[PDB]
Image: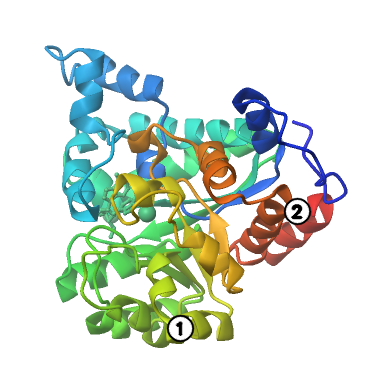
């Protein structure tokens, strides 16, 4: 892959067709911060697992897709999160998990990603077939390292723990303890699923930072919530370095100023927000006004295996419907690298290699 430099960003895209634009999108040196490894599979990988383990013998491929994935516009975040629970059928042994991780790296390299942060949920992957969380973790860390070494370190991978099991104090403590225990591999900690104001778990998140682990949580995504409290908590109480989505920052001048004052970056997932019905359309997506207001934002794919969309698709949508330029896209990837949780050298070397 012959990546675009900072000295090649004046390209005239107006005469290119969709196909030729995707070559440019691919060639952009991307840093992706918000993507769930759990569902980071191609359609063929997914159908290969469903067939190999004989999970849906009476369903056709089209039916398998309607039943497990989320490729069409839905109602809400809540609907997405509850539907996602059924494809946990695939997390059947530790080989499926290791392969998932390895292929995810390969797919991201081919899309032109150079610094990839993946996040996974131990509880998501473990509960269906009662798999051991540490054995999952082992499988995940082997797969990712397998792929990186095979690619001669042409893509670098960071790993984040999306902690869950539930919102009981015991479950959330356990989830944070799993991450802390594996902090040699986890560069950050997340909360996902149904959106929550995490104020009752400040004690746990303090602990995680005490242990040297950066926080990026999902907050300010779900537009059905009649307040912005999850955002205030993430910023003031959790001391997040980044926010997953955080698009509802756009609804408050006070929060716009707060995130800029703290140099917090918003992990924006354009297509996710459309499909999960958190913006009216891509035309009206808040990323535009947030970028224009000086908020640091990056571009991400979120759940590519469920959406049947990839990182470059999100770039296409931002170009076509919101008129982001190549220079804008390069700026955001520079921000994504700078605000990455991986080793500071890896960042600096990537920065001077491309940006
Ligand atoms: O499709 C998915 N991929 C990855 N993670 C998911 C998905 N659906 C839900 N979670 C959610 O992430 C939680 C962390 O607080 C997971 O346990 C689960 O609730
Ligand atoms: O709960 C979630 N899990 C995984 N990806 C997501 N993207 C938005 N919400 C979620
Ligand atoms: Zn264990
Ligand atoms: Zn997400």
Residue situated furthest right in the rendering: 7
Please name whichever residue, 324 or 55, is drawn nearer the observer in this view of the structure. Answer: 324
Mark closer to the observer (2, 1)? 1
The answer to which image quadrant residue 279 occupies is bottom left
Left or right: residue 72 versus residue 24 is: left
| Residue with the mark numbered 2 | 350
Q: Residue at x 41, y 44 (%)?
A: 37
Q: Is residue 3 above or below residue 176?
A: above
Q: Residue at x 74, y 31 (%)?
A: 1
Evaluate if marks 2 and 1 touch, with contact meaning CB atoms under 8 Å apart: no
Residue situated furthest left in the rendering: 58
Image quarter where the C terminus lies is bottom right
Q: Residue 281 at x, y = what percent?
A: 38, 49
Q: Residue at x 56, y 31 (%)?
A: 106
Q: Residue 340 at x, y = what percent?
A: 60, 62
| Residue with the mark numbered 1 | 253
Q: Residues within 10 Å of mark 1 (few under 14, many from 20)?
A: few
Decide if residue 35 is in sight here.
no
Decide if residue 258 is in sight here.
yes
Q: Is residue 152 above or below residue 43?
A: below
Q: Residue 274 at x, y = what percent?
A: 35, 48
Left or right: residue 136 versus residue 320 is: left
């Amino acid at each position: 892959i012959n990546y675009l430099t900072k000295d090649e960003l004046d390209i005239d895209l107006s005469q290119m067709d969709k196909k030729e634009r995707y070559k440019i999108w691919k060639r952009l040196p991307k840093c992706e911060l918000h993507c769930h490894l759990d569902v980071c599979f191609s359609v063929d990988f997914f159908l290969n697992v469903i067939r190999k383990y004989n999970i849906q013998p009476n369903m056709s491929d089209e039916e398998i897709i309607d039943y497990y994935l989320f490729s069409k516009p839905g109602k809400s975040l809540d609907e997405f999160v509850e539907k996602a629970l059924r494809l946990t059928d695939i997390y059947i042994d530790y080989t499926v998990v290791e392969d998932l991780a390895k292929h995810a790296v390969f797919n991201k390299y081919k899309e032109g990603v150079v610094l990839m942060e993946f996040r996974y949920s131990p509880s998501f992957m473990s509960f269906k077939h009662n798999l051991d969380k540490d054995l999952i973790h082992e499988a995940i860390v082997k797969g990712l390292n397998e792929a990186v070494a095979l690619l001669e370190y042409k893509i670098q991978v960071g790993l984040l723990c999306t902690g869950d099991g539930g919102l009981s104090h015991e479950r959330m403590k356990e989830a944070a303890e799993f991450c802390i225990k594996h902090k040699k591999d986890f560069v950050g900690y997340d909360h996902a699923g149904h959106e929550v104001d995490l104020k009752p778990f400040k004690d746990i998140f303090d602990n995680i930072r005490e242990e040297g682990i950066s926080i990026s949580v999902h907050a300010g995504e779900d537009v059905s919530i009649p307040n912005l409290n999850s955002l205030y908590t993430a910023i003031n109480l959790l001391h997040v370095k980044r926010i997953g989505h955080g698009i509802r920052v756009s609804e408050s001048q006070e929060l716009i100023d707060l995130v800029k004052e703290k140099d917090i970056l918003l992990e924006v997932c354009p297509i996710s927000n459309v499909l999960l019905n958190n913006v009216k359309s891509m035309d009206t997506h808040p990323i535009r006004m947030l970028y224009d207001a000086g908020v640091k934002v990056s571009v991400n794919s979120d759940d590519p295996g469920m959406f049947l969309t990839n990182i470059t698709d999100n770039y296409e949508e931002l170009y076509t419907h919101l008129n982001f330029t190549l220079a804008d896209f390069m700026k955001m990837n520079l921000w994504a690298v700078q605000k990455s949780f991986v080793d500071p050298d890896i960042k600096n070397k990537i920065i001077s290699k491309y940006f």
